Image 1 (cartoon, each protein chain N blue to C red):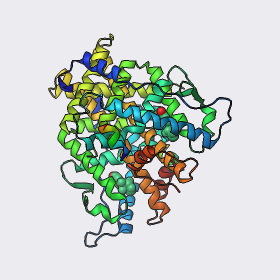
Image 2: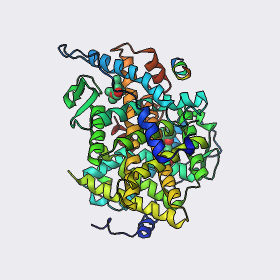
Image 3: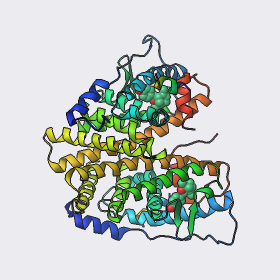
Image 4: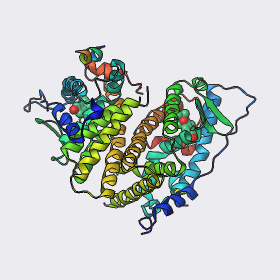
Length: 9
Length: 9
Length: 237
Length: 237
Ligand SMILES: CC1=CC[C@H]2C[C@@H]1[C@H](c1ccc(O)cc1)OC2(C)C
Ligand SMILES: CC1=CC[C@H]2C[C@@H]1[C@H](c1ccc(O)cc1)OC2(C)C
């Protein structure tokens, strides 16, 4: 889930 | 349309 | 005019008096539910509620001053929002239950009888929960309800709109007045006022979602909706 | 930390969090098509999404939420937040929508996509409401923050409500220091938040529209938009 990663990154 | 009738009444 | 000419607590009284009644469904409680019986019951009710709310809109300050065509528009946009916050209001003291009618009290688990309906129940329950957290009062509620009628159609309509905004402001004054004499601090009045009006945003969402569910159910031809329902429904697309 | 920020420190922190204004890849000497327009503005929305995530975690009290909360909040509000940006950007260009400094679309150019012109209309009506109301950059960043924290909060949060109360204080702070009297303060604050209800409405219309463009597949959407899109439930006959 791209969102999750853009948010953790 | 039934709304118009009810309204003007 | 005369809507501009009410006192704060003359506004509240007029609205309290304008309230429509609470209707019963034709629910035979000895019979369990199916999808078609559900919808049927719930659409039959909304249809009968539609007549009262119209005769209620005529008794909300300023509304009757608006042209017939502008009145139609406001109603076509808000009817289900108005139905919804009423539902939410009746259910406030029935945690986990939706009081569609005193004889039709729906558990969230029963919402599953109708396909897709369960999400809508969860939102409606949460809103009712929110009202409870906040301990929403009858005087404010009737103010909120009127706001929905005057606010939902307005930005898609000629300074007929200016008059609508004046009454909107008069209804704000009214709400502040209520909280002021409820003993709220100046800051606590702003916050509450914002908390209430922010909820209308979620109520708009529920109605959009709900609207689509209804359109879905008709396309599916699961239950035949009244001819008022099908008009209010087609106004949206 | 968000809670112990002065109103002033709140406004500044938000103004500095502002995402930049992005550009279209649009090349002006090429003609438009339902496909090319939808391509240009989903391309634009998709790059804007990346900057919104960033801005989100620079909104006081947002990094303080569980990552799943963060996700839910953004899945719910993403289109409203692009829309309020759009509407604010198009303020000084009445009759037109500044999607990008080199993508100024007028009313007629919405016909290029079927089902787009009515959302165009709602959108123009909103920025027009903003301009008429003469919304200030500082007030705008508060509104945007409110949508992020408010839209999803009821479909799960004291922390979120306390932050939401802090942003409300700040809005008033701004009005109180702009010269507005006490009733003028609470009226403007009502008119502001009542507009958020319309933005929620346009968001649901535009989301159904987007899913429609996927369904008749006039353009391949990005992986992120599809995720955004799929956090909502929809259909298209
Ligand atoms: C008959 C309906 C069908 C679909 C929508 C709108 C109403 C129904 C409703 C809502 C409030 C009310 O007072 C009566 C019916 O709610 C749902 C099921 C969500
Ligand atoms: C590409 C889109 C298609 C349908 C919806 C959502 C976005 C588009 C949009 C809005 C703001 C923005 O910054 C980027 C795209 O707005 C409309 C056209 C209303």
